[PDB]
């Protein structure tokens, strides 16, 4: 739960917080609001701006709603309250909802869906006639009298973008669109970039980019899109690419990349796609997430929020915050309290302080809490320092060909590292994200010596459970280790590799050794024929690479026979259960591989010839012992 040091308040209080509702005649009355939903909090020029649905009468989507704002110039000491956007007043369920926000300069751009009288769900409408996509510009103005700083925000007249909306995309006939919800972006080229969600006539849902090159005068829909079934997209920019992180009801969350401003989308199979999901079993309603790029401790990272939803459906208990540098993925922790139902969420890093505005739900009455994430930021900084330190350390090792070293120890795409630190049953990731689980082992410099049944370590992949941070390995990986065989096996015994989920004891790619002192590389389901020669007690360098559905095993820098073969046949992504180190098993054959393994490194890409050599030549230099 919310860390020690951290605190929150109910900033938008259900059945309590009033908003200045304007009547038809133009008189203002403070009007109490049943539920506050769909939060975004942003910084505009030193001013915090918090945007929400004011669901006046009920929490239900197709009800009477207007866009509320609270803003502060003293970082949440005090707030002023507004309705930024009024609904049409056509009926008892007229609504403006699902605010998607862009900050450029002292301006906010708010995109909402406006509906007049439908009582059913937007994806289910018969046509788009009840609907309008509305753009509203706010301008923030500051000024100080008598020391004290004040601000005002003036909201312009909404503009419908309906006329900009094509009737068709690649033959698909369009119905409606809304923003993806939450904080969107100004790209590095100044483009206003909205991720949008689109419903076709059929009610299918897919996502796209809608962008403006001209501070919002005109708008273009880029050519690429998601698979059907993606909603409420969140976008950030990272190393010259848009990254679009999608809601997927009833399956795992799809993440795409585009480096041509949305024209071409490529699924992020090698980093973030299918890592996050809706529930432990992946078959539940999903939920909106915030997805924001920030710079912490001099390092650019992405921040991502989503409930675990252990309760299922819409309950959305146990809101977590993850932080990723697109290689490692760290769970900062649960930011909601206890088993409370949370929901939609927003996150903001401002003046070196970290905040969330998110939903809490009891009996489907919703407030929005404003959270000072004090302990979380402290942990985040520690983790970032660890990442920069070990990367700087590794990259600063002089490798054998001394200004006149070999190529640097590869660090780009280094996800994880198991070295000196270990206790009883845990082998610690140096990068502090995913540890290995250990049995029948004894500590040695930079690793472990296994003896007894199931002696070995399990570095979980699918076995991470819900959030699958090593999902990338199903698409590509390099696994590296330094090994000694300590005792001859009776026949054939395992050493290193990737196991597959499911019946049998199938492996994607692996290495075993046998009684005749030969190696037995395993390329998918192919027979694990012997090759080469080793001797007991001698240190070998082992590298496994898999990319483009092909695998290669290297010993002391050199590929073993069969290397380059196809390890996965078919278009279906492998499902790797774990990496095994030694012969771990909690069942089956009582494997007892007598090996010692140290310095196990995992990369989210197939390393090149020179990188492999460099690792082999630097074996002795990279340990944390
Ligand atoms: C979120 C929510 O799930 O709690 O759902 C949205 C949609 O119902 C959902 O994505 C189905 O298409 C709501 N909006 C609308 C316009 O229906 C969000 O406001 C929110 F309700």
Image: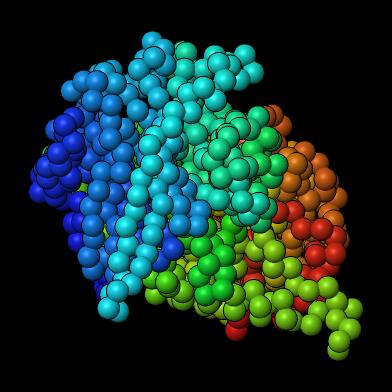
Residue furthest toward the bottom? 402
Residue 269 horizontal side relative to residue 529, left or right = left
Figure disc tally:
0
Residue 24 horizontal side relative to residue 554, left or right = left
Q: Out of 533 and 132, give the one closest to the viewer.
A: 132
In the rendered image of this protein, does residue 15 appear above or below residue 458?
above
Q: Is residue 514 visible?
A: no
Instruction: For the C terminus, give its image quadrant.
Output: bottom right
In the rendered image of this protein, does residue 558 appear above or below residue 469?
below
In the rendered image of this protein, does residue 233 appear above or below residue 477?
above
Q: Out of 49 and 228, give the one closest to the viewer.
A: 49
In the rendered image, which quarter is residue 480 located in? bottom right
Residue 618 location in percent, x, y? 77, 76
- What residue is rendered at 12% in x and 45% in y? 30
Q: Out of 72 and 466, give the one closest to the viewer.
A: 72
Residue 357 location in percent, x, y? 31, 55
Q: Out of 226 and 76, give the one closest to the viewer.
A: 76
In the rendered image, which quarter is residue 500 located in? top right
């Amino acid at each position: 739960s919310l860390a020690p040091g951290s605190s929150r308040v109910e900033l938008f209080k259900r059945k309590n917080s009033t908003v200045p509702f304007e009547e038809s005649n133009g008189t203002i009355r403070e009007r109490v609001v049943h539920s506050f939903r769909i939060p975004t909090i942003v910084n505009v020029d030193g001013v915090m701006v918090a945007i929400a649905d004011a669901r006046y009468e009920t929490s239900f989507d197709n009800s009477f709603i207007e866009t509320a704002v609270k803003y502060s110039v003293d970082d949440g000491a005090t707030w002023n309250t507004q309705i930024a956007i009024k609904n049409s007043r056509a009926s008892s369920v007229s609504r403006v909802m699902d605010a998607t926000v862009i900050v450029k300069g002292n301006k906010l751009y708010i995109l909402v869906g406006s509906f007049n009288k439908t009582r059913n769900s937007w994806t289910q409408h018969r046509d788009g006639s009840d609907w309008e996509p509305l753009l509203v510009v706010g301008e923030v103005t500051k000024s100080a009298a008598n020391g004290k700083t004040t601000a005002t925000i003036s909201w312009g007249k909404p503009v419908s973008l309906k006329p900009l909306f094509p009737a068709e995309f690649d033959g698909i006939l369009t119905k409606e669109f809304i923003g993806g919800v939450g904080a969107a972006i100004v790209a590095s080229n100044g483009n206003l970039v909205y991720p949008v969600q689109i419903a076709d006539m059929g009610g299918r849902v897919f996502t796209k980019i809608m962008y403006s090159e001209d501070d919002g005068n005109t708008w273009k829909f880029a050519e690429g899109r998601s698979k059907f079934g993606c909603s409420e997209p969140a976008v950030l920019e990272w190393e010259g690419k848009l990254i679009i992180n999608n809601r997927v009801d009833g399956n795992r969350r799809l993440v795409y990349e585009s480096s041509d401003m949305g024209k071409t989308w490529v699924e992020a199979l090698g980093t973030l796609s299918h890592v996050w999901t809706n529930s432990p079993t992946s078959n539940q309603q999903d939920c909106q997430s915030s997805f924001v790029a920030v710079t912490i401790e001099g390092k650019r990272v992405m921040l991502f929020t989503h409930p675990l939803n252990l309760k299922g459906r819409w309950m959305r208990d146990r809101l977590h915050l993850w932080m990723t540098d697109n290689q490692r993925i760290f769970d900062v922790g649960q930011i909601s309290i206890g088993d409370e139902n949370s929901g939609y969420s927003s996150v903001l890093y401002k003046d070196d302080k970290l905040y969330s505005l998110h939903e809490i739900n009891t009996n489907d009455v919703y407030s929005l809490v404003f959270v000072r994430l004090i302990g979380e930021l402290q942990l985040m900084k520690s983790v970032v320092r660890t990442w920069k330190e070990e990367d700087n350390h590794l990259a600063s090792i002089c490798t054998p060909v001394k200004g006149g070293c070999g190529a640097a120890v590869p660090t780009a795409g280094l996800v994880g590292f198991l070295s000196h630190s270990a206790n009883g049953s845990v082998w610690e990731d140096v990068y502090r994200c995913v540890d290995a689980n250990v049995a029948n082992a004894e500590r040695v410099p930079n690793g472990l010596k296994f003896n007894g049944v199931g002696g070995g370590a399990v570095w979980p992949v699918a076995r991470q459970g819900q959030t699958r941070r090593y999902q990338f390995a199903n698409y590509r990986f390099t696994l590296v280790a330094t090994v000694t065989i300590d005792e001859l096996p009776k026949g054939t015994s395992p050493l290193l590799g990737a196991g597959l989920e499911g019946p049998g004891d199938a492996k994607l790619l692996g290495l075993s050794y046998d009684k005749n002192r030969q190696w037995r590389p395993l390329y998918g389901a192919a027979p694990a024929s012997p090759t080469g020669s080793w001797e007991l007690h001698k240190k070998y360098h082992v590298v496994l690479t898999m990319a483009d559905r092909q695998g290669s095993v290297y010993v002391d820098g050199q590929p073993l026979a069969g290397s380059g073969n196809t390890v996965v046949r078919g278009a279906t992504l492998p499902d790797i259960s774990h990496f095994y180190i030694g012969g771990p098993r909690s069942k089956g054959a009582p494997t007892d591989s007598r090996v010692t393994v140290t310095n196990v490194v995992l990369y989210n890409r197939r390393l090149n010839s020179s990188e492999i050599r460099t690792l082999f030549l630097s074996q002795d230099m990279i340990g944390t012992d």
